[PDB]
Image (tube, coloured by chain):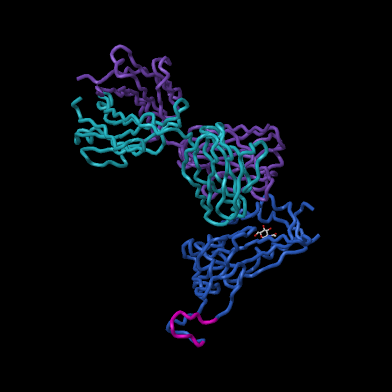
Amino acid sequence: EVQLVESGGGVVQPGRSLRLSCAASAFTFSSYDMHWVRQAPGKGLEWVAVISYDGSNKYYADSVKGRFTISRDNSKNTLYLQMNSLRAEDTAVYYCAKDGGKLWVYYFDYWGQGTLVTVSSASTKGPSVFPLAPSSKSGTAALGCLVKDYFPEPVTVSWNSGALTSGVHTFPAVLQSSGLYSLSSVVTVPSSSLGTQTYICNVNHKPSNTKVDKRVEPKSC
Amino acid sequence: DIQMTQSPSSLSASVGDRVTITCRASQSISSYLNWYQQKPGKAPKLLIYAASSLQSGVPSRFSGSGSGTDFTLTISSLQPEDFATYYCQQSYSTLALTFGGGTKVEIKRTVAAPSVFIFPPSDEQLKSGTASVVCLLNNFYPREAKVQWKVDNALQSGNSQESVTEQDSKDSTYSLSSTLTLSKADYEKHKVYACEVTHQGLSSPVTKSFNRGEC
Amino acid sequence: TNLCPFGEVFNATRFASVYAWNRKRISNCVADYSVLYNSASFSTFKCYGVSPTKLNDLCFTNVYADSFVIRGDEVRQIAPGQTGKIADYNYKLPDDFTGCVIAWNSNNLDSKVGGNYNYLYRLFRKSNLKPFERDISTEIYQAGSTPCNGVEGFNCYFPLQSYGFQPTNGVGYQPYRVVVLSFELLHAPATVCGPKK
Ligand SMILES: *[C@@H]1O[C@H](CO)[C@@H](O)[C@H](O)[C@H]1NC(C)=O
């Protein structure tokens, strides 16, 4: 029974500052070296920094040395990570971790669930939903909605207000070069039921308060 | 600096199989290597620390080995709650901790032929300015699948970007969408738009194409 | 009662060249590592095989403080498994090294307006140095088929070469002072201990 709770993550512009905080519980916090470890979206894990059990020692990776700052308050049982001059490379989910200390060297005994830190110079934008219409294949067909140009994550996507569940795939978004995100959501249906059954996708972007219902119907010619 | 090469990049294995993953170091680490588990989305979790010491609360089926550069993690009998990406992590360089690339363990199952559909840019998108040609690879296995855009028989590269779902909970199949993004002016300058797909379950490459503005 | 003489190792008025790297033996003293902790003036500082935080509470049999001077581009060679002129011909660390390496820019100290040429390295050697080897032989390096009878000339080169340390050199060629703290624990009494007695 060991718990770590990250908080303080959020969207932030380049060159700004941001304060992260890990709340420890159910062990002697003031007697273990503490770790920060980040993981970029889709990339691998990356060690960030270390502070000693007494807070006298502070060590950093070469990618963040002289630019982050680790600290800790033993009375409050908290671990702080001040992030000054954030760059785009810092966009990642950050984790706090207990050392364990059973070795002369650092290892990672228990992991917190982490908090998201996105660095981007774009304002919040409403998504643009576009249809993806089929045609005469010849089997079964498929159709979808393109949730293009929005920021930040996430966007919730459903089909026929939740009535259409099986056969649906909503894909992870992709940070296109404009700093905005693009997302694809699709569903497969038998080639016959295209005139009778109506198809409408439901997109909701809470960070922008933009709800959109888009009709999807086959290409006409 | 120390880099860690973990191999294979991705493997397929069913339940009960004796799984083994190799982690190799750019230079000698005595035994300060660590094996971590990470489910998709969940936080990482310690499995093995210091070459071959089982962490408290980790099932006995897990076991490390090796010393020097070539280390090994072994699952004697795979279990369903173990399908996850496994990382290796060296510690010898204390103030420069580096991890491995990882080895996702996907549920082994029969080869599945993808259903390849292509979607032209909607008229609503064309009036805005941009144009996105979508190509869908649906329900297939394994992950490895080549998607190649052709525009007037011209091989395209760098114009698009893919996205793949995790191994689906129902049929254990993957899915992929290439989003070929380009401007309006670059859209009418060309006619044919094609999506060539190569996959292990295809006796020959499959192409799905359309001509601009003909339906 | 007696602290370990870490001050005369760092704050020494002058260091030696890399080929004649100077060794201080640390034994029979309480190790105060806080001189490493507070001094943020350190450009490069990496510990291998042992943690710096978990160091002030661990007894070792002997400590070995090596000190010398190199240039910035060469600093990354002071580590196990590395190769290069410094690692191969001047100062080689073993692959199972357990210690720490510290280095800081001393351009203000080891640079003269005319170029301080006092610091040297070994440019040629018939074989790579064994770990912790200190070669200072000035034997004329034989490079060609014609043997060198202690004379220089055609394929007879002097094995040592000088650094060109000027205040206007780029940070790559600026002089960095370097100290390697190696640690050894043997089947023997531990004479060096942190404050955790
Ligand atoms: C070496 O000098 C620095 C200041 O230049 C000082 O802070 C440090 O304490 C000195 N070393 C020792 C062991 O006192």
Q: Pick the quarter of the image with the N terminus of chain A.
A: top right
Residue C168 picture location, percent across and down = 47, 65
Residue B174 picture location, percent across and down = 41, 31
**Residue A8 showing in the rendered view:** no
Q: Is residue A147 left or right of residue C73?
A: left
Q: Nearer the viewer, residue C59 or A126?
A: C59
Q: Is residue A93 left or right of residue A166?
A: right
Tell me which corner region of the image, top left, top right, bottom left or bottom right, holds residue B196: top left
Report the chain shown in blue. C
Q: Residue furthest right?
A: C1
Q: Nearer the viewer, residue A48 or C176?
A: A48
Report the chain shown in cyan. B
- Is B131 above or below relative to C84? above
Q: Residue furthest top?
A: A196
* Residue stretch in magenta: C139-149
- Is B57 above or below relative to C3? above
Q: Residue at x 39, y 29 (%)?
A: B139
Q: Residue at x 40, y 25 (%)?
A: A169
Report the chain shown in purple. A
- Is A19 above or below relative to A188? below
Residue A76 picture location, percent across and down = 69, 34
Q: Pick the quarter of the image with the C terminus of chain A.
A: top left
- State which image quarter holds ligand 1: bottom right
Tell me which corner region of the image, top left, top right, bottom left or bottom right, holds residue C193: bottom right
Q: Residue at x 30, y 28 (%)?
A: B117
